[PDB]
Amino acid sequence: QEEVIALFEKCRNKYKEGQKKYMEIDEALNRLHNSLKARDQNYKNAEK
Amino acid sequence: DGALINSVLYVSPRNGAHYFVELTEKHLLAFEMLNSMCLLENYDHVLLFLECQFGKSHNLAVIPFDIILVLFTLSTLSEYYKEPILRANDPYNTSRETLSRRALKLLQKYLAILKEFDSEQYNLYDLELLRCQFFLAIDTLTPKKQKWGKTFKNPYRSYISCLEQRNTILGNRLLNLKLNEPGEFINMILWTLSNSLQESTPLFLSSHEIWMPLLEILIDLFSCRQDYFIQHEVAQNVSKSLFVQRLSESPLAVFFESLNTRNFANRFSEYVFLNCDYKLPSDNYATPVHPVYNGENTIVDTYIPTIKCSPLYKSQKSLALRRKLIGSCFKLLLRVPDGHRLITPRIVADDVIQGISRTLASFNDILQFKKFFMTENLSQESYFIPLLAEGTLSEILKDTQECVVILTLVENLSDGVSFCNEVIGLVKSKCFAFTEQCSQASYEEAVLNIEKCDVCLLVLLRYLLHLIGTEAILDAKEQLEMLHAIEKNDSGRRQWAKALNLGNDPPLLYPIVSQMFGVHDKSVIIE
């Protein structure tokens, strides 16, 4: 039972760190998407 | 007539064009800037260039003819089926309006500017240059030979046109190129006339957003071009036989040459009134129609159709467009010298009048009939509408009554007394009166014929008032007797109103003539 409860502790820690990474990557991806759209519009205007 | 047809001060006639106007430095720079922007597919800044200086200055910014063609093609990129393309071209919709709508609005505003020459508002050189550009566009939009179913010439050597190296704007082929194909001009006309009354959302949107405004603009431009051609391109004095040959080359002659079919009269009558309420006679073959620009008949997922038009609105607009087509036909015809007839278009005024009368008298819905015969400006449509009214009246009297009384009302519009005497003759003959041979079972169709008869007579009466006014309605006993005979026909119809065949009251035109020129029911209520 001690091994299994320690297994759950490490499982929950890995779960929380995975969600932290997932939020970080999703936030970065959304910011990059919006920035890319803005940069595309800016480049099209400048080229024209 | 006006200055638009008789202002040739700044023209520099050439072999291809007689309206040609040379460019000045400012206009040359404007043309170069517009073409340069159009090359970069920066249509938003083209429209902004034209709109930012519209109505804010005395001098006028003239649209080049090739930019006019670009705007014509842009007007076919309606949002309802081209939303992704338009959003991709202009992701930041700074004008909060579609490219199609802005281009169409600019086209209509510049057409309005061209239709009246305000020499005080705009200097004459700019107006003449604008006329030259529009006429060049129209001459580039010459229809191809009709099919049952040369690249680009720039008159100006001072600048390179944007259309020289391209033929599509945003995936849509240029309007001139699309219509300069053997069976596409007639196809476009039939498409818009059929979809003007469709209840299907994509077809009605195609007619209402793209093709009816464009057809309005094209018909107006062809009318102006026809007037300019008759004023200048002809040789003034003529042996009355070379003039017919020149008229066969007129812009309206080529316009309607793509509509000749086999028999112009009946096929034209079906074409103008396509998808109307009239019963199709003699089992005429159905006219195939297809969308002009790829998926005009589809609605893209992103667009949500959120506009509803009442049936009266759609019918009114469609019938007005049909009247414009018929009026252009009659404008071409009325110049034909008497006795002679046109060579290239096999068209006769009597044949067209009789065909339109046959189609009108076969209407089973009164709403479209009235929409056709109710016009906001009597003087504009004065040269053919009375003829159609009298012809439809004659045909209705022919089918309703075995004795066809000859109607001379059109030339009787000159003398009100003669018109009133003829009305008295028709009503005393009981032809205009409600007919006794009509049975009880077929009372509805007889009512329809009578109400159409009343509409035709009302149109002729409005034209009579337009040509003579209200001067001797009671001073001349003839008009008083005409009013009393209208009352006699009122009593005749009231006889069967009391016969109680149907609860609905029959059409009685006494109140309407009273409101117009019956002096409010003569002395029934006045005295």
Image (cartoon, rainbow, N blue to C red):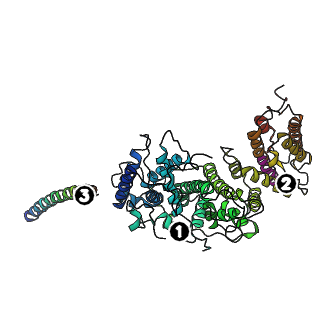
Depicted B347 relative to depicted B397: above or below: below
Q: Residue at x 62, y 62 (%)?
A: B250
Classify the position of the C terminus of chain A by image quarter: bottom left
Picture coordinates of residue B283 (x, y %)? 73, 70
Say what amino acid the circle numbered 2 marks: Leu
User: In the image, which residues are magenta?
Assistant: B440-456
* Chain letter for mark 3: A
* Chain letter for mark 1: B
Which residue occupies the extreme bottom position in the image?
A: B149
Question: What is the crowding at mark 2: few (fewer than 14 residues within 10 Å), some, or many (at least 20)?
Answer: many
| Residue topped by disc 1 | B180
Q: Secondary structure at mark 3?
A: helix
Q: Secondary structure at mark 2?
A: helix
* Chain letter for mark 2: B
Picture coordinates of residue B430 (x, y %)? 90, 48
| Residue topped by disc 2 | B397
State if disc 2 and disc 3 touch (CB < 8 Å): no
